[PDB]
Length: 392
Ligand SMILES: [NH3+]C[C@H](O)c1ccc(O)c(O)c1
Image (cartoon, helix red, strand yellow):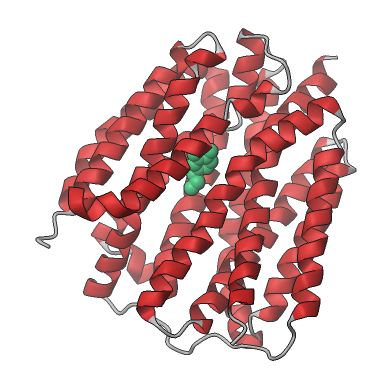
């Protein structure tokens, strides 16, 4: 029946959540720098913005188990709507807060909102569709919104902030979220759909599988690279290249564009190149690009390594999703939500361990040494993907 509306709702929710996640990057560190300064200074700022950026991932990791039980007992629509309500509250807080603590609280609330939406929307979208093969395409469209949301984020936030102020982009996000919530609450309230009773193996024993662990570690490291890049590159650019405030999003644009291109091409080229081969090459490439990043002096020197990072991360994600699915289907019993639960756990871990440790290491020894360390870790972990050597 009216299932395309549900697909649209989930797509919009994921896109808006990722947009709100990635708009913060060019604006918050510069704003805190301007407050404090107008060296131990900006170093304490790096070590504090690391925690501020890791707060959302930590809260999401903690609150993820509870939302599944809640939607099991009560049904998807209430968590789906609560996600938009909490996202609206968090967006208004960021726009009208100046202190550090209120920014931390807004990020924490965004964590719960993101987790609730990511769980309940995926559950509804999986439940509503009838064909498993048709279910294959619709997930790709849902994740496509996530990749597109992180694309227009940094440039829209940075250019709008530098010309108008600190409030315009957050107000725009508030308006869009309110419109989406109005659509959700008005256009459809026909029935309250409950999740399927087919529950697979618990995530604990699933994570206890060594092959699942290898795939999860690969994904976690590949995402932790860019997760550590995100909250420190603006500060390094401002301190070294004395760049204006509108270029801090143009710096991150090529990475997102390359992520889109790499995901799209290798979602078709993976099974012809061999999935383990594609993942191995992706890990090696992202390691080398991360190694090459600190050698730039101008943005023109940052154009290429960001391209490589985005391309390789797309390769790794596209190669590692179906391998996770196949391993879960073979060694255990499988439901469509188990793969996304594993992927969400890996992503939240990569974004929770990245920024804090990255800030601490950058304060201790510097930015280039941190990038060298993470690149070498990626290079060393790359050959471990050989154990995904399934004969088909
Ligand atoms: N899965 C998303 C991935 O971490 C990511 C995030 C932001 C980006 O600009 C990107 O290229 C990739």
